[PDB]
Amino acid sequence: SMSVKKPKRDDSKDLALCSMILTEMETHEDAWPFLLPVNLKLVPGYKKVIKKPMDFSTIREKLSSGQYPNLETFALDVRLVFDNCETFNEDDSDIGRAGHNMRKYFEKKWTDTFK
Ligand SMILES: Oc1ccnc2ccccc12
Image 1 (cartoon, rainbow, N blue to C red):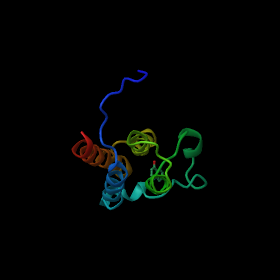
Image 2: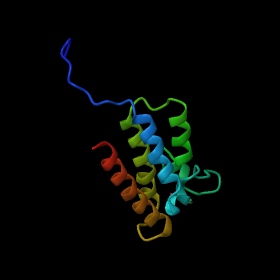
Image 3: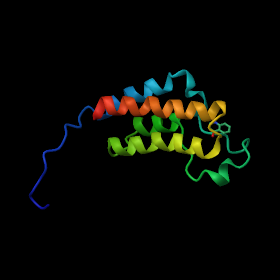
């Protein structure tokens, strides 16, 4: 409260570390569905069903231009990619499986790096 502050974690390396995690995700062999925005003109249903599209290139641009105020807003956008994937794809499809694999991969990096 006013004039009563918690010790807070050193956040000075957060930007660099999120960038490293994102690089590791960008170079994963199962990242291919998620590298660019889904083409809303070519994929029926996507625009109407998925209210907030997100992809790795869009996260990279936001990270490079100061659009994440903190590391938690970064994690929310990463998770959004995989939540969107689960919404639109059957678990037992190539894309569906890719999404589960990448979510697992991300969450371990996240825990190992920050928790
Ligand atoms: O949900 C998706 C994620 C990435 N790519 C996709 C390509 C076509 C149809 C759905 C997709």
